[PDB]
Length: 4
Image (cartoon, rainbow, N blue to C red; front, side, top):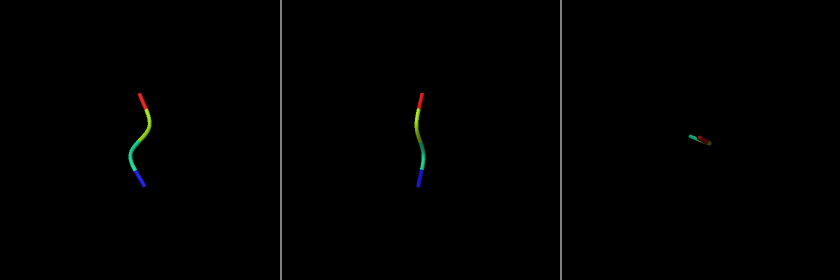
């Protein structure tokens, strides 16, 4: 999970 990568958010940004």
